[PDB]
């Protein structure tokens, strides 16, 4: 599904074609090289790295994008797709 509220602060990155022996200590660290990772989670053949600053998230991709990881190459991209931008009007 989809998160919902396009608006967000932190960044999320999705990974595919993961290894069976892939460990968080590996994936996370790999992403930590770009920026201060928040929370990393490995999946069957995919994963998800929660970044803090976009500048780091965007890079972590252009770099870890199509990179032989754990022997097999994984595809890294934006976890959530944002089409419509939102500033953030008042609420009070």
Image (cartoon, rainbow, N blue to C red):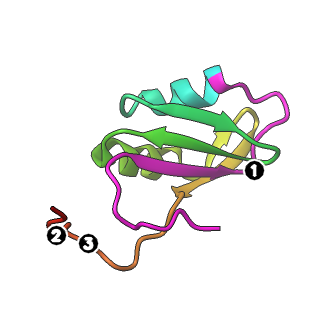
In the rendered structure, find residue 17 and report the number of the disc placed on it. 1
Q: Secondary structure at mark 3?
A: loop
Q: How much space separates mark 1 and mark 2, taking CA atoms?
A: 40 Å
At 58% from the left and 67% from the top, the residue drawn is 2
Neighbour tally class for label 1: few under 14, some 14-19, many 20 plus, Cα within 10 Å: some
Most extreme residue toward the top is 25
Most extreme residue toward the front is 92
Instruction: Please report the bounds of the magenta region as a residue range.
Output: 1-24
What is the total number of numbered labels drawn onto the structure image?
3
Residue under label 3, please give it. 86
In the rendered structure, find residue 40 and report the number of the disc placed on it. none
Task: From the top left corner, tell me how far across and down residue 74 is, in percent.
Answer: 67, 49
Task: From the top left corner, tell me how far across and down residue 55 is, in percent.
Answer: 28, 46
Q: How much space separates mark 3 and mark 2, taking CA atoms?
A: 9 Å
Query: Is residue 50 placed above or below 16 in the rendered structure?
Result: above
- Left or right: residue 91 compared with residue 33: left
Marks 3/1 in contact by CB < 8 Å: the verdict is no
Q: How much space separates mark 3 and mark 1, taking CA atoms?
A: 32 Å
- Left or right: residue 22 compared with residue 79: right
In the rendered structure, find residue 89 and report the number of the disc placed on it. 2
In the rendered image, which quarter contains the N terminus?
A: bottom right
Task: Give the mark, 1 or 2, whose residue is nearer the N terminus.
Answer: 1
Marks 1/2 in contact by CB < 8 Å: the verdict is no
At 54% from the left and 41% from the top, the residue drawn is 49
Seen from the viewer's position, the closer of residues 77 and 48 is: 48
Query: Is residue 69 placed above or below 76 in the rendered structure?
Result: above
Task: Give the mark, 3 or 1, whose residue is nearer the N terminus.
Answer: 1
8 within the magenta span: yes
Q: Secondary structure at mark 2?
A: loop
Magenta residues: mostly which secondary structure?
loop
Task: From the top left corner, tell me how far across and down residue 17 is, in percent.
Answer: 75, 50
At 49% from the left and 68% from the top, the residue drawn is 4
């Amino acid at each position: 599904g989809s998160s919902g509220s396009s608006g967000k602060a932190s960044t999320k990155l999705h990974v595919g074609n993961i290894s069976p022996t892939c460990t968080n200590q590996e994936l996370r660290a790999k992403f930590e090289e770009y920026g201060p990772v928040i929370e990393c989670d490995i999946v069957k053949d995919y994963a998800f790295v929660h970044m803090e600053r976009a500048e780091d998230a965007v890079e972590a991709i252009r770099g870890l994008d199509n990179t032989e990881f754990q022997g097999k190459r994984m595809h890294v991209q934006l976890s959530t797709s944002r089409l419509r931008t939102a500033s953030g009007p008042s609420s009070g």
